[PDB]
Length: 8
Length: 304
Image (tube, rainbow over all chains, first blue to last red):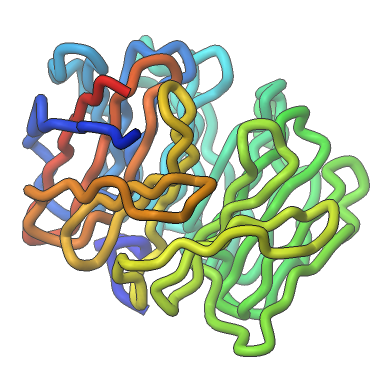
């Protein structure tokens, strides 16, 4: 994945 | 007066969540980055796939154009940025020095500098020509969600999950201004207005705010969308009516009248969080892109 595509 | 954006193209081909779409300043191209580790280039007016740019070892969270539309910079979970020649597709430089995911990136208008933000809580300023890291700003106390130059490159605005927006002097690296909110919700996005006098800040309480940073006062608030979990790109749309555009976690694109704060249009069709929107520099065109259940980019066109 990528950090932007992962929820906080 | 309300816009009438209508779907024109759906661009498929990314194999994981799309993370960022950006129009080239010259209006010819859309670039998309993805968790699938790829950059794709598409024609802005016909939606035609142009090329795939590859080389990052892990997924990408952001991509940005140089002012002359010849270069791209990307920010990756592999802790690097890469500078790419768009014509050749070749990696010209790998920018090394962050110690965690690189999340966000931008060229300055002169396009001799790149600014980056990272989960390592720093903002870095890089020389485009050499790839040297010129400055490391200890900008925030949590991951940095956005970085953006103002119109002449003299200021950088950063935002963080620490709840702060900060304005930095590019030349010195000194913090000139910190905007705080007592509730301190995570700030998930920030960007200067086109003229550089205002900042648009997203917070993870389903709120966008327009700030006058010369005075440090919030002038407008935009609500109605859903934003609690992702760093969603928002925009000033200026080719026609003066709008604020944002993605949303309810799978819609939201469009507000900047001055009245009323929602003027909601664009339906994505099947996952709209993580990214972009506005074309000269035509009333919006690009939107969505997460893992969708993986597509949509191009929308309005008469105003």
